[PDB]
Image 1: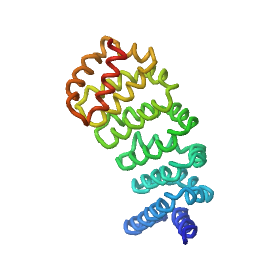
Image 2: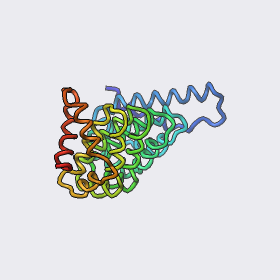
Image 3: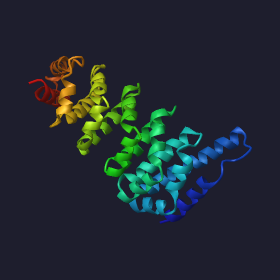
Length: 264
């Protein structure tokens, strides 16, 4: 194979201290070598057993402890990506990564990072940790993760807005016990504001999320019916805009369900 040795060699590169006094060429070479190590680890860690071996070698300790807060964006995003790759398919690794305080650091990257690729990979990592994990989602909530997702849907870069909205929709389907909290947090209002923006692909997920919040949930219905929100007007205009087009059928179905559920 040669895979255990690659993995150990890569961890040795990544375990080295940042070079002390360094000129620009030394610093740039050093960063490329660490980037390459993370990439080679990612290749290995698509396999679930490699992923587990990686964790057994305390790789997640190193990524969470040092690389999510590395100076260079290229290290941060590759670190976030590798966390997601390893944890995506393995419940045991999800739990280990959560116990290492990864979520607080990932949310900070998603919410604040100057580099968009870091944000996207952070969101990927978060999605892997939180979707099939009741404890990870509880912690996500406690860490104000739904507000982080909301600000991601509110900012400009379309890739992040679609992926954030997609995650919110998924969490609401998978975890309906949280509709109350989300409604009380004023998510109906914040989601409906997103529906007011220029029609685009993330709208489908936004309206899917709203659908979850009203489905068998009187508080969601009440919020949707609030006179100032103006949601009926919005939904009826959206229905007429989408109704002849086969490729918006799912967003249209969400609008229709909201109209049925909330407005006779």
